[PDB]
Image (spheres, coloured by chain):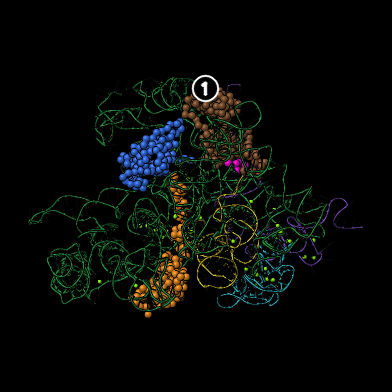
Chain colours: A blue, B brown, C orange, D yellow, E green, F cyan, G purple
Amino acid sequence: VRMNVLADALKSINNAEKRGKRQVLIRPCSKVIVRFLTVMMKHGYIGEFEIIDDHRAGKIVVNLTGRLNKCGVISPRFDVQLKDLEKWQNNLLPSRQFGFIVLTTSAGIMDHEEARRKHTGGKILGFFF
Amino acid sequence: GRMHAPGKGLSQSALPYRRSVPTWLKLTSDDVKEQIYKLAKKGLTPSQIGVILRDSHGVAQVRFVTGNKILRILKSKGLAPDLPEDLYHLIKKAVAVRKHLERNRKDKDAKFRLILIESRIHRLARYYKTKRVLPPNWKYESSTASALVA
Amino acid sequence: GKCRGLRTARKLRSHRRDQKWHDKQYKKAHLGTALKANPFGGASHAKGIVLEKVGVEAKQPNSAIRKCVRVQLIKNGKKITAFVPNDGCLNFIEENDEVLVAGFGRKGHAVGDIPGVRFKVVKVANVSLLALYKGKKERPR
RNA sequence: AGAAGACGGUCGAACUUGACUAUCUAGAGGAAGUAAAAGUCGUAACAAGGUUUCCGUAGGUGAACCUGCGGAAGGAUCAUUA
RNA sequence: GGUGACCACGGGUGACGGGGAAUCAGGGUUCGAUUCCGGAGAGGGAGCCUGAGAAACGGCUACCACAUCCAAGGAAGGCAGCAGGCGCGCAAAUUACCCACUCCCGACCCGGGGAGGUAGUGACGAAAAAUAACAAUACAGGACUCUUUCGAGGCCCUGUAAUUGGAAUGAGUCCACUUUAAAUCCUUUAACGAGGAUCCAUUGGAGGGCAAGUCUGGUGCCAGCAGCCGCGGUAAUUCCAGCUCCAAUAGCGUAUAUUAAAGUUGCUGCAGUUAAAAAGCUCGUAGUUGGAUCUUGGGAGCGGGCGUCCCCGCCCUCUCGGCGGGGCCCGAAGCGUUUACUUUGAAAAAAUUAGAGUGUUCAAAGCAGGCCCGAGCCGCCUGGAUACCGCAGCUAGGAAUAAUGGAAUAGGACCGCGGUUCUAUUUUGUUGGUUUUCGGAACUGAGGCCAUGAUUAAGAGGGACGGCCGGGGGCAUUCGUAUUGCGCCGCUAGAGGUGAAAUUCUUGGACCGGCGCAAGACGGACCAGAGCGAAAGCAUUUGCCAAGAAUGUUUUCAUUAAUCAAGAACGAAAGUCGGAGGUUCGAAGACGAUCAGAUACCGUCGUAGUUCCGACCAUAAACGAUGCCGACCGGCGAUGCGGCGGCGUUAUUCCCAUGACCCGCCGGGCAGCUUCCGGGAAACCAAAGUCUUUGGGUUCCGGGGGGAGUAUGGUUGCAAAGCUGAAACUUAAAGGAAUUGACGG
RNA sequence: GCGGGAGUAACUAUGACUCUCUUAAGGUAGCCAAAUGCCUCGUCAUCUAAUUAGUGACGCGCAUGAAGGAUGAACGAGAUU
RNA sequence: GGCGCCUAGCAGCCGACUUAGAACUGGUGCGGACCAGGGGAAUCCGACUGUUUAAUUAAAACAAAGCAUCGCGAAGGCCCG
Ligand SMILES: [Mg+2]
Ligand SMILES: [Mg+2]
Ligand SMILES: [Mg+2]
Ligand SMILES: [Mg+2]
Ligand SMILES: [Mg+2]
Ligand SMILES: [Mg+2]
Ligand SMILES: [Mg+2]
Ligand SMILES: [Mg+2]
Ligand SMILES: [Mg+2]
Ligand SMILES: [Mg+2]
Ligand SMILES: [Mg+2]
Ligand SMILES: [Mg+2]
Ligand SMILES: [Mg+2]
Ligand SMILES: [Mg+2]
Ligand SMILES: [Mg+2]
Ligand SMILES: [Mg+2]
Ligand SMILES: [Mg+2]
Ligand SMILES: [Mg+2]
Ligand SMILES: [Mg+2]
Ligand SMILES: [Mg+2]
Ligand SMILES: [Mg+2]
Ligand SMILES: [Mg+2]
Ligand SMILES: [Mg+2]
Ligand SMILES: [Mg+2]
Ligand SMILES: [Mg+2]
Ligand SMILES: [Mg+2]
Ligand SMILES: [Mg+2]
Ligand SMILES: [Mg+2]
Ligand SMILES: [Mg+2]
Ligand SMILES: [Mg+2]
Ligand SMILES: [Mg+2]
Ligand SMILES: [Mg+2]
């Protein structure tokens, strides 16, 4: 059964991006997915996304801008401290010039640069570059 | 997929987005409640009550029109069945299969289906004992289950 | 696939230490039966008494009489065969000599065309075979 | 004030005996596995290997093997006509 | 009672534990007998005196094992302290000097200390660093230059060899000083001390990997080399040597343990169709993992510049606010859950690790040191940081993520109002009488109010219901020809079988034809890359019995789920046991052929079996050689089932329904074709894709080939056998996919 | 009821193998100097100081052998060490 | 009957044997007589229990369950006469 809604959504986005589609539909929506997509949209890797609201869990239609390479997930949400965030960063990112790691922190869902900026750790969510 | 079958069917019910009661429904909440009471006294399980109400009296969702579910209404009035409907039907099926099997000893297919049904019974009973619907000491005995159903 | 849950460490480590017995190096180094079967008993070198001088036929593509000595080790009394590794160093070997024997190169495995020989003589009568071969010092008459 | 000594109790070494358990180890005879000799007999497997091969099971034969029953194609057929 | 699959208990350890060490992307893997801390022991045990402290052993007692002296009556032992012996070994130092330093003990400034310091042995290992430098001649070379190769010097850099050829130094001899308890060593410093500067650099190599010779002489598959490929059988790039080169250098080779290489143990991060590999199938407990949903946006001046950036201010309650009665303020009580998480702070031995400062002559080190001294400085300035220290425990901020709960038989929250029992203090100050609703706590009855209180109903699941659908299963029943045998009838000499025959049956009527009878098997054609079932498997008719997927659903419950060690059900064929039955076929067996032989292939016969009922067994190339659940990622035409919508044809009927076709759509299946989605070693695969751009959940399982699925132990079985399952030893390949050739009865 | 004779493997020794004669078929699975083996107190091992005894093993077995062969607990006033 | 709470059960009386534990004690003797299995490792045969030569053989012999074969449908099979 589906146990990682964020993982399913991220895999769907990655496959649609690889196939070159202009829009992608991810069926199970959640607050975590919306926050992840908001982070990606603020960093410009995706376009606008619109939430179709049924009385069940909603759906999301994302406009793909074509500038995404990978948007994978780290399924076991490991506890990430600021002392090992660098090791996570150079394990998951293509380079130190670009690429972001989204981790859920006590201050909210945000990328690793903002996490280090406001000096907090959290649980790993995923990455995109 | 199915719990005990290699089937991946999709046949379901698509509840509409409009939760509002249709304007052509003249039945009020108390009227629907009285209909449910009459059907429950006649002996219908909540699934059958809902089916009759939807087919004949034109009510779409008892929860939408009254604010409460059928089992909640029955339990509030005090005439809900002692066993849950699905558990009762599983025990009924198991009793029927055992009755067939005690005459057809070579029906190994029936023995396999009986094992599947009893596994479902035990899992559902575990769920109900967790939710405290059933007594904490409730146990399904194959010998004494025949007097509980039909 | 493999399990990835946050509290699967017990299963991960149990599976790892179960599967670690299936490679030859770990099994040899941690079972102990190889240590018992090793004539040296986990020692780099050993001492022995030359029981005999023998010649061993080389393998199929080669054709030579490799010069070896049958040696009984002073400790645990095990009998082994040790190659004498130079042109004329068998002449420096006689009966009842106290020879030092080392491994023959690849950790208890036969080397080259010499079948079933895992040791070689380093010193005889507390003088090095290299020294005797180069003539830097003489047999203790 | 009092030593030797004695009855009893308690820790209890040690000896004898028996049991259990670890390794090492002899053994008539039997039965295997490796290696080398162009040793003897055959030619079962590779081609349709000259009875297609192989699996499970059972019986039989100097030896590879053979045969029955069910299976596989990793076949020598991706196909055979209203 | 207590402990156990969250691994108890038992066994092993070549286990003292830790601080730490090796290796070094990250993660890890090994090692810690060893100087610091903690523990234990003093030949093995055991028991004690004394003392604050011992189950002390440089204390005692006894036994055991060793072992000393003896006048044989007795007596005395404990170096895993410092040295030093023997033994064991591959393996490890002097029976030296001193309490001078650091400290310890004592009645104590004074004694003692094999603690400890010093020296000796010491290529364990680490740091520095000699074996030569310069100049001038010849012969070369240079972007050299001077006339345009010709010849030279107004230059530079090597090598060859010399009466060069005179400069600098040590390594050593050795006086003194210094050091030191006394010496030694180092640093100073006299004097000797270098031209094969003979004051002499070695260890391994020169086919490849891997830097270096297709040199020469011997040997001739011998000797030998060779970690691996390999060299050597008379012209050796590989052996034995000479010469010459190569690498490191006062070090280098070898053996062994271990680390990296090894993404060949894979958490990061491996694989499992064909290379080794997914259990025959399903259920299923522990374990692991689990859908969505509860506060978001609005504010003001400081503001990563309302500068529509935003340090950022945010536009819990009640108790004496310590500046019985002030707004001049911030303390006492609780958290409208409990946790995980994250950040901070504390507490975390030193040494070591990283790292700050410091010219030890540089460095490894060490924790030192530096400023002036004009000679009066009748002395000044410092340092002896800091970081890390897992996990567990403590504290304070945050509340995203994840678990967990609150009100459903209201036994709910909050505001009060009745009626209950006690009591710290009352003071209705002379004591005593005390009223104390005094203050709060004791249970209990009737109210008001809360918007009174149940998130939604997953392209999650279970269940109900409707019409179907299907070689799904069991029981009974019906039919079909065929085969074999038998009985009658007809006519005949062959019939059968084969590559050819023969065994065999035949004037006794064999075979053949006809009519019947009996028995037991088997359900052809229809029958398909069609269906159903968890697989194994399932195909004559009809009836009965339960079961089921898919579909339809504006039905119901509301997370009840996925995968699953242990355990359980079923599980082709063969085989086993008991009872029936035994037509055909047919292991074993017999015979005839074939053949060199023929225990076979071919033919004739034929036992067990093949059939049914009941009980075992639990194995197959049990195959898709391919785990399950979930999501995504091309096209196309079909097919099976169900549903939905449409021109028409057809069946009867008078029209629609309902069947049979035709055209589509949807869902679940068996598949097929095609594709530069992508993957893969490729064959190939729309899964074997979405994998170095590596993480959806979870189960099993492989680690070169053999030995070997063997031995042994355990367990199951009537047996056959099934499950679990090594090691010694051996080997450099064994294998997979494709290409070319050769070959094919 | 269930056979003979010859030759044959790179040391010898055996004979997997090959020839023939013959039978109705040539003794298969097993088991053994057995309560069944003459030779015989067979040969080897074990048990003892010493064993024509016992046990284990071997098998061309005068003359073992399958409705009886071979095993196997329990039992036996059975025979033996 | 207004009249009260054994409700963690009390009070009195009566009664067999049996078991367990402790102290003391005797010249270590105590199932004190009587009653009352020596044990173990194997081989052969017979499965076992049973039976047998009264008056020399109790056995390995006979029987046995089990297994297999044969005859017979009554005008019959087997047997007496
Ligand atoms: Mg064959
Ligand atoms: Mg063949
Ligand atoms: Mg130890
Ligand atoms: Mg230690
Ligand atoms: Mg210590
Ligand atoms: Mg002690
Ligand atoms: Mg002591
Ligand atoms: Mg020198
Ligand atoms: Mg050379
Ligand atoms: Mg390594
Ligand atoms: Mg691998
Ligand atoms: Mg394979
Ligand atoms: Mg479970
Ligand atoms: Mg969730
Ligand atoms: Mg014929
Ligand atoms: Mg079967
Ligand atoms: Mg039978
Ligand atoms: Mg036949
Ligand atoms: Mg999984
Ligand atoms: Mg292997
Ligand atoms: Mg025989
Ligand atoms: Mg005999
Ligand atoms: Mg005899
Ligand atoms: Mg005797
Ligand atoms: Mg015997
Ligand atoms: Mg034998
Ligand atoms: Mg008897
Ligand atoms: Mg018997
Ligand atoms: Mg009698
Ligand atoms: Mg008599
Ligand atoms: Mg008698
Ligand atoms: Mg019998």
In the rendered structure, does residue B114 fall within the stretch colored magenta?
Answer: yes
- Residue A26 drawn at (x, y percent): 43, 37
Identify the residue at horizontal 45%, vertical 73% (top origin).
C63
Q: Which residues are magenta?
A: B110-116
- Residue E446 drawn at (x, y percent): 49, 20
Image quadrant of residue E399? top left
Total number of numbered discs in the rendering? 1
Write down the chain letter for disc 1.
B
Q: Is residue C6 above or below residue E30?
A: above
Q: Within the displayed image, which quadrant is ligand 25 positioned in?
A: bottom right
User: Which amino acid type corresponds to the residue marked 1 in the rendered image?
Assistant: Leu
Q: Is residue E500 above or below residue F62?
A: above
Which SS does the magenta portion mostly show? helix
- Residue C30 drawn at (x, y percent): 45, 59
Side (left or right) of B59 relative to G79: left
> Among all residues in the image, which is located at the extreme bottom?
C141
Residue labelled with disc 1: B25
In the rendered structure, does residue B8 fall within the stretch colored magenta?
Answer: no
Near-viewer residue (C73 or E77):
C73
Side (left or right) of E353 relative to F12: left
Identify the residue at horizontal 45%, vertical 76% (top origin).
C53
Near-viewer residue (B2 or C135):
B2
Identify the residue at horizontal 51%, vertical 27% (top origin).
B61
Name the element at disc 1. loop
Q: Is residue E553 above or below residue E83?
A: above
Whether residue C80 appears in this view of the structure is no
- Residue B123 drawn at (x, y percent): 54, 39
Image quadrant of residue B47? top right
